[PDB]
Amino acid sequence: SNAMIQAVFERAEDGELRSAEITGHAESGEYGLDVVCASVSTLAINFINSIEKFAGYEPILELNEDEGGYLMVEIPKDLPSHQREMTQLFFESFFLGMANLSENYSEFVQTRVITE
Amino acid sequence: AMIQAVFERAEDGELRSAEITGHAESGEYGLDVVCASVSTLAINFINSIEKFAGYEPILELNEDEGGYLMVEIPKDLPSHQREMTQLFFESFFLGMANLSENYSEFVQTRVIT
Ligand code: NA
């Protein structure tokens, strides 16, 4: 079956992380889900906030809390090297966080990588 | 659930440690959502250092009486590991600072310098 929270990370053939699409993480009540949603949301929001503060640009974003939550973050093409490298560092940390949530709370979150 | 976070900065601005108290479950109950957010930031910080920077930070964990976590960076880090550590640590601080704004009734974040 499919978990409530779905997280797909897109990687280029050279390993560069291009985007993350997360669904199902909007705030939705009890026995287990709320705390996992909070953890996913914290990682996702801090990822974006860290890019904006430290890398110094705004990524491409699509958001909606409506049908259980939707977040798509996409890295602009042709970023200068320092922005690329900081973004990749944070993106790898975000992926690790989600991968570890999917390992330890596997009935709530699934995390996958796709190629570009 | 009064969560207190204190981050230590050296004279040049480098982050050296964070100490967090009050984030233990429970609960159950509104507060555990805030605790889970704080724990996620702390644990991902630690895991990121270990995976990407290639060393173990110094860590003290006590689950008792509201919970206690202290993470400290080794003093003599080679330059490759030092810079990467700082980006992760700044991100960790930003997350906690933003949590303290969004959940200002439950989380307080400070810096000691
Ligand atoms: Na590339």
Image (tube, coloured by chain):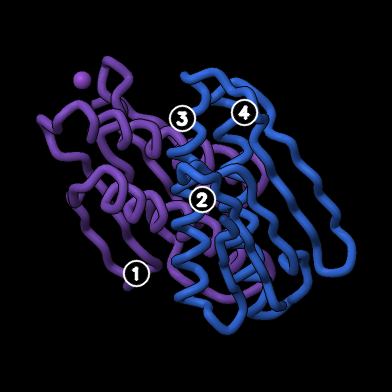
Chain colours: A purple, B blue
Mark 2 is on which residue type? Answer: Phe
Which mark identifies residue B92? 2
Q: Same subunit under labels 3 and 4? A: yes
| Chain letter of disc 2 in the image | B
Of A110 and B80, the residue lying toward us: B80
Q: Earlier in the sequence, mark 3 or mark 4?
A: 4
Whether residue B54 can be seen here? yes
Q: Residue furthest left?
A: A78
Distance Cα–Cα, label 3 vs label 2: 13 Å
Specify whether B102 is left or right of A114: right
Asked if labels 2 and 1 touch by Cβ distance under 8 angstroms, the answer is no
Q: Nearer the viewer, mark 3 or mark 4?
A: 3
Q: Residues within 10 Å of mark 4 (few under 14, many from 20)?
A: some
Determine whether the beta carbon of the residue marked 4 sits less than 8 angstroms from the nearest atom of ligand 1: no
Q: Same subunit under labels 1 and 2? A: no
Q: Earlier in the sequence, mark 3 or mark 2?
A: 3
Residue that mark 1 sits on? A67
Q: Earlier in the sequence, mark 2 or mark 4?
A: 4
How far across and down, in percent of the image, does residue A2 sit? 50, 48
Mark 1 is on which residue type? Answer: Glu
